[PDB]
Amino acid sequence: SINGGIVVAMTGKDCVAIACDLRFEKIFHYGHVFLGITGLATDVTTLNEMFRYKTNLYKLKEERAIEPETFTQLVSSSLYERRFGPYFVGPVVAGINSKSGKPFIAGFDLIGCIDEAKDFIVSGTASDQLFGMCESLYEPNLEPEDLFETISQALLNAADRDALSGWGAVVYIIKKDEVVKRYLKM
Amino acid sequence: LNMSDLFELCESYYNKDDKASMIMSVEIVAGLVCGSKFMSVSDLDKRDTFIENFLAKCLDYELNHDAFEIWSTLAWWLPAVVDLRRSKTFFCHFINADGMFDRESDAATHQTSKIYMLRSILMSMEFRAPDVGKLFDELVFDHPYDQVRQAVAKLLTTLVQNQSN
Amino acid sequence: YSFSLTTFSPSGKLGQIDYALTAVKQGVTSLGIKATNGVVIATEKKSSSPLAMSETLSKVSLLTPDIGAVYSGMGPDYRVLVDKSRKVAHTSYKRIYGEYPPTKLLVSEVAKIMQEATQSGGVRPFGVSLLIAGHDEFNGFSLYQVDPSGSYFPWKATAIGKGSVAAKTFLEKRWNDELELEDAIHIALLTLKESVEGEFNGDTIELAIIGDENPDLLGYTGIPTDKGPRFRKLTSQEINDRLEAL
Amino acid sequence: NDRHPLESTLKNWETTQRQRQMEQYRQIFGIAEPMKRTMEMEIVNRTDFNPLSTNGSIHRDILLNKECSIDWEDVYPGDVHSKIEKQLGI
Amino acid sequence: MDIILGIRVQDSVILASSKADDKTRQLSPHTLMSFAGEAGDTVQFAEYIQANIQLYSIREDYELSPQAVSSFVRQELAKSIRSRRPYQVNVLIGGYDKKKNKPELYQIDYLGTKVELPYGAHGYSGFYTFSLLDHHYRPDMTTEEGLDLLKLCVQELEKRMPMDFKGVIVKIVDKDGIRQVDDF
Amino acid sequence: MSGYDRALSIFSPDGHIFQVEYALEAVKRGTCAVGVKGKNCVVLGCERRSTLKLQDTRITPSKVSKIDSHVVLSFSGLNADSRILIEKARVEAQSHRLTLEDPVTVEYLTRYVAGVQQRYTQSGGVRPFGVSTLIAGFDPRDDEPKLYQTEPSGIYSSWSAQTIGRNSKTVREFLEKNYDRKEPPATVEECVKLTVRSLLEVVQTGAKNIEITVVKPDSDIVALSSEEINQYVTQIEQEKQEQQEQDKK
Amino acid sequence: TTIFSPEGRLYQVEYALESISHAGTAIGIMASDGIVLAAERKVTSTLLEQDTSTEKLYKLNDKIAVAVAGLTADAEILINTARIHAQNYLKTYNEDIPVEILVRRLSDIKQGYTQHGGLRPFGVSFIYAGYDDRYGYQLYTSNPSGNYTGWKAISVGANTSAAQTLLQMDYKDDMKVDDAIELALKTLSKTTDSSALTYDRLEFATIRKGANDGEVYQKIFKPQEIKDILVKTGITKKD
């Protein structure tokens, strides 16, 4: 129900990550592609319904699941359709090409301009505290366990250190043939 | 097998609730009456007393619509292929079937089935029917039910036709 | 209001579509072959006069940069389907997914257009059978046939038109599951050499391939991400050079 | 009103552009030309009913000169008895 | 006034709605909605929802889960705002899931924001109900403890707002379907 | 308009031998459907054709269809059509309340149904429905049982008992002898017993083929199960044995 | 032209029913713990692409499948409409579509194409399959008329009558999915016009539960998996 909240996304050697605020995850999945949406909670849920629909129909019509880059073009072209009255959101797609193995992260404004940073992505209000933390803690080509470590400490440090009893974070760590969802509490 | 092994097969297939099981019972009855040209005098008697009790159990109470279709099919088809005098109790069950002309009987559909089964037997024999002169004194032409009054009119038709040659 | 066409004949047949398959059966033959690393589609060009310039009558057509088409039947029916097929690829799929549709999704959409013409008052079914051939990252190379009914079929090889039964018998006799694109081109040139009504050379024959990407034909450099057209239409000199290797 | 400036214009754009074209053809070519063009469109629209397909028609795109052009309206589009009793009158 | 309160218990959902029409609609044998807001739009929206779930229940000879009625209510609430300036509406749906034997409670905002709850309120309340509920609330609370928590909650609301709200109607969904319970 | 009346031989106008007559032929070939009123109930009953051995009974539709909490519809003729005809009536009734703060009246559920059937007769090379229906129930705030029949032409009529479909002559003949309009069945049990006797004369085999729905005032709609109609069938068959053995000779 | 025969019967529906009576055989069987679908495919073409992903059998959503007898061009229009309705129900109610609601949905569209004279009817018969919590494993059939019926085992298309007789004598209410695998393969081998059954002539699928309590899984079998149930069953066209 809480409006806003933050999502963070990050690349490692053959792996991806998606951190998010709990206390209803912002982070959905459609097969191997993950979508963290920040913003108005009604638009986060309406977009979940809309992309679930579109991606189930895709899987039915095309005999295979929607790849991270294709899903990026679908989310941007769907968001653009809403041009005069958009979805009040910051979507963050992620996922590992099932035919290549390359990490992918992208994020968008409310009408679908594609960012495609090769390192990390942020979305939500007060992003630029986390943008500094994430630029400070990131390094290229991590293993999955260090990749979990850098994204989780970014979330903890940029966290409101005054209300850490109200805390809770979900970190999806996504690999080629495996996905682990760690819930994380203090 | 005995004859009675075929009287227990006929009994086992007679099942009011399944039309096809019920047909196989009436096909064994038809076979028992048709097979009469090959039967010995004691097997004849066994067949006649089995047929008497079997027909009485099937037809004297609680006839359903699918049973009436199968028995009306036998009543048309059987006299056209075997002489009903080969078996004392077959033509006798239909000609002497009780309450077949009782005006007070509210069982009018049952009574109509008896009249139409007898009519089918008399239509299938025609000028070879036995002395049915007792029927002319028994006919109602005054039944309260419309169904039993129209089986009587169609029966007088076949009785007049049987005399008319 | 007693209004429909292509109603059922008492033997369980659609009738008008049957007459539409007799128009297809009268056209100049076209054929298609799928190989291990590419595909081929081919046909003959029949001149109404030798004064006609058959550089203008293309029969083999680009639907998307990885998908080709060819027909047998009524060419006018085929010029109108090809331009709807092109519009469909862009409007239904490229403008939603930023990538072109597969050769099973575009064949379904072409077939949906031909089905709607059978189930209508006011319109006759199409007088064309279409061979659609192409490539996609997850399905790989594919060839399909579409008939006036709106029925579509995946084929390893096929032929349609006058010479089609003798072509399909040659295609069964010659096809094997390890063909390559230079092999399939030779088999297709051999098959049209039997079906040809007129003269056989690089000017009378249409031939296209969906093969490797050709980065020359993209017409701009700087973006390796964009591999460049798989669909290539053989030049009349290449056809004459391969017809010298025959 | 609170309603977007462009909304009523883009709602009626397809109708307005053809209605404006027919008036130019009346003016430059005379009443016969829009009388011909409206009757062709009437035959195409009225003889082409199929309750499960709403995606336009192939001959209407030839008639309207839309056979190689995409609008946002063609990439972003938007009961068989209810269709039947509208096509025939209730 | 137009207050709504909610205290779901181990084996029931308790919907309390302000006394005035109830502004709470029986959607089925085991589902209530309560609603609050701009009196024209909400009453008409609730009857549209009720007619669609009654039509489903007749057309199927079946019940609709408290989830499915709730997501239908959010989808129709959101779909009603796609040509309109948002009307003030809040929906509090409580029902009994007879295929899993759980009572369930949902809140929907004017923007169409589903939240699945232990307890909820709208219309005429601040942190006084929410603090009083969070201190006393338990996952296994009984219906009699729930009615006492609701009495504490209505007393806290009465003490802070001594004007006459004419008490509230309380209604319960459980194994036995809708029970209207007398409370004061 | 039919048979031997023919002036100077004859020739046909626009007239009788027509699509609606062939829809009436489709209705007569569909299973027997019956309804009888009582003092304070109405019972609708139907013939199932005897189910095939591989058919699935728990999901098989109840033939008598509830249109609303107080209205019930049964039919003979084409099933597919009756499914399309019940959908229109159900949404028409739910829409009635949503726009009139009033549940649909039984007479408005009969004028609407026959009314929509009449529009598919009138014109257009859209065919009429091969369906005839019984519509039964109660109005709200009343205790009078109602029972209507509708026909493919869009004609409708009120009956205190009626039958449609296969063999319905013989059933209507039995009802005219057993239903007294001065003293109708005074209790639900007798009303159900009368419908089971009425159907027992025309159904294929027995208790399998009958199925009944009882409507009562204040939305008390109640399908009877196989086991409940088996105890009615058995009681009626007991009374047949009792009547036969109470022969005096 | 959608006018009645003088018996009150529809000529076009009867002719569409003649068309599907040629259109290849399909069997469905409802075990105590899953549904089996199987269909026989007349591969008279060597160059037709077997190991194409579908022809007779299709997914409608994550727990519903169909078999088709009839025109595949007609079937694919209905199949897409059913897929759109399944996802539009899931979008509305957040819950997976009940099988009865979808099977009868396609039975209401197919009746409309039989009433209006501008439309020919659809030449298709569907043997639906699926799971939901309202009932459990359900097996339904629907035909060009818009009639639909619930079954424990059923055949459609060619050789229906021989297949129904073979089902009726071997079907048991308490059988397991592996017994329904065996039965559907036996039935088709005891019904086929082709000399013996083989993996490319056969389309197969199942609707089991698996090991994990929340699962229902719809394996539409690839050719190699069908070869394994063929060699296990004793149909076994094996080296």
Image (cartoon, rainbow, N blue to C red):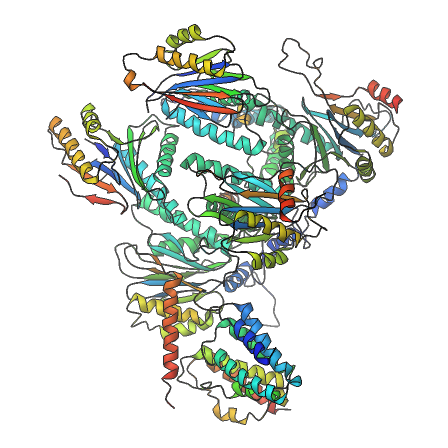
Q: Is residue G231 left or right of residue F52?
A: right
In which quadrant of the rendered image does the N terminus of chain B lie? Answer: bottom right
Residue E62 % position (x, y): 38, 47
Q: State the image quarter where residue D27 is shown.
A: top right
Q: In the drawing, does residue E180 fall left or right of residue G1? A: left
Which one is in front, G220 or D50? G220
- Does the image show residue E19? no
**Residue B82 at x, y percent in the picture:** 64, 83
| Image position of B108 with respect to E114: above or below | below
From the viewer's perspective, tell me whether residue E129 is left or right of residue G84: left
Q: Residue A85 or F123: which is nearer the viewer?
A: A85
| Relative depth, front residue between D74 and F70 | F70
Tell me which corner region of the image, top left, top right, bottom left or bottom right, holds residue F234.
Answer: bottom left
Quadrant in which residue E37 is drawn = top left
Task: From this view, report whether residue E105 is shown above or below residue F158.
Answer: above
Q: Where does residue A21 sit, x and y in percent of width and height?
A: 36, 19
Residue E8, percent across and down?
25, 36
Q: Identify whether C59 is placed above or below B127.
A: above
> Which image quarter holds the C terminus of chain B?
bottom right
Q: Is residue C129 visible?
A: yes
Q: Residue at x 20, y 29 (%)?
A: E133
